[PDB]
Length: 96
Ligand SMILES: [Cl-]
Ligand SMILES: [Li+]
Image (cartoon, rainbow, N blue to C red; front, side, top):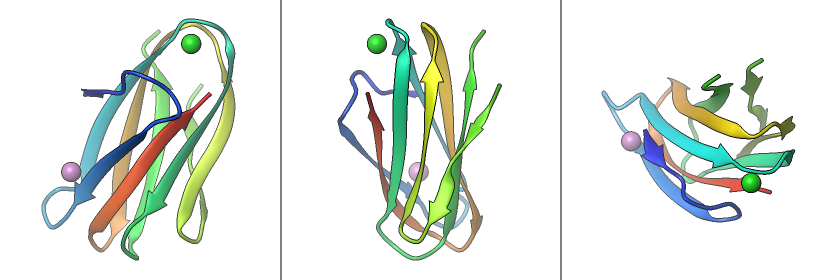
């Protein structure tokens, strides 16, 4: 996984051709709501799935944005960005 070292900060990714999955992780130190936002930089079928290291959460696809909010306990989390159709690039933010 690519470590996302802080919140409210943009990551760039790419899912062209054979590249169908990108892996991230982040750590929560204080309980609270996170807003995970993917912004498509190309039109294609992309979403994400969050699961804890120790309930899973999915992105909700709203046009160019694929996002959701969830209250997370302290711990490590894994975030899979993956495609289901086509190819393209994206930006990703874990807001808190
Ligand atoms: Cl935190
Ligand atoms: Li990629």
